[PDB]
Every structure is written in C-alpha cells, then in structure tokens.
Amino acid sequence: SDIEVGHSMNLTNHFLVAMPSMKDPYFKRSVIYICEHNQDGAMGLMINAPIDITVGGMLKQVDIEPAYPQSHQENLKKPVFNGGPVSEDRGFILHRPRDHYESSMKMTDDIAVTTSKDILTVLGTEAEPEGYIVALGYSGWSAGQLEVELTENSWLTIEADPELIFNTPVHEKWQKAIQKLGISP
Image (cartoon, rainbow, N blue to C red; front, side, top):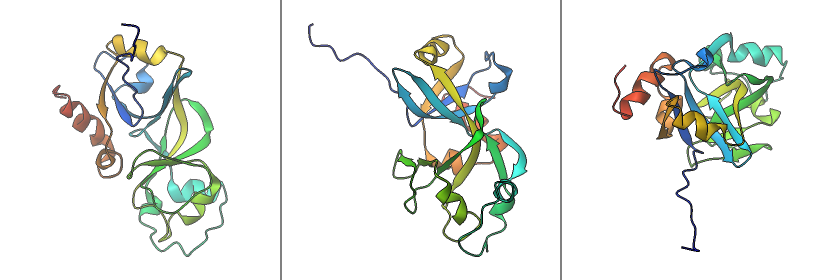
C-alpha cells in the first residue's frame, strides 16, 4: 500500500501501430519503432515511410568519402526513410549491431540506433550493418502525449523485433503488424 510500483508499461523497443481511427494523416498506416520513452516525452522512428532519395543518394549529397570500396551497390540503391516530422535535417541509423560507432544506443542484441557520422563511411561497403534503415527526422511526443494518444484509440502497440524492421517489404510492414494484434487489413 505504501509500496508502489506503478503498472507502468515503458514502450521503448516497442512498435506503435497506427490504427484505422488515426488522425494525423502523416501517420496513417505507420509503424513506429519507439526509441526513448521517459517522463519528458517520447522519441520514435517511422520504419515504413520511404522517400525520394536513395542511400547512395544522400551519401553523395552529404558528400561522405567511403572508407572501403562500395562493393554492395544493390543495397546502396535502396530507399532512405522519413523517420518523422521533427528534425528532418538530422539522420538516424536504425540497424543490426555490428561494429562500434561513436554515437550509438544499443536497444537489443539485434537493434541499435547510431547518430554519429562515422557509420556512413561503411554503407554500401562490406563493413555496413547486415540490416539498417536510414531515417531523416524522427517522431516526437511531449511529456505524456504518448500515453494520451494511446488511450485515444490512435495506436496499438506490440513488442518490436528485427525481422519487421529489416526483413519485410516496406509497404507490408503495417499489414504484418496489425496482424500480430488480431485486426486484419
């Protein structure tokens, strides 16, 4: 009774699945990997909103001189993603843990977020992650707006896993998500 624990929930390393009754059209049928979730708001990365720029595209744009020969070339043609409306000029790399990068936050043995530029010099090369998403800008929620929108029937949530982020056709991520929640597309 004096011993509190709070039912809590903590949505980090969790996917937010847009629900049919979703408002912000921006998020209509979005799947969001939640990175941070403290008492000062939330930070997530959309994982299925691809944009008009390719990985090699922004690599050339940001003008990053590659460390090793870029032998891959196929994945270098893949799309870059819009991670959210906030800080669209910033890049976030959601990937499978491989080598050590300066600014990086490991989430699981299979998912991590790197924000240092050092990682860009291995993209297209054989030193790149075995699965990564290049996202510009991120999704943000103030103090407890997350909780609210949740109880507002706006989203559904499932624990995140790597296969949905790196091994699932972009335009298929959503459908396969709500699937795990029972609801059918």
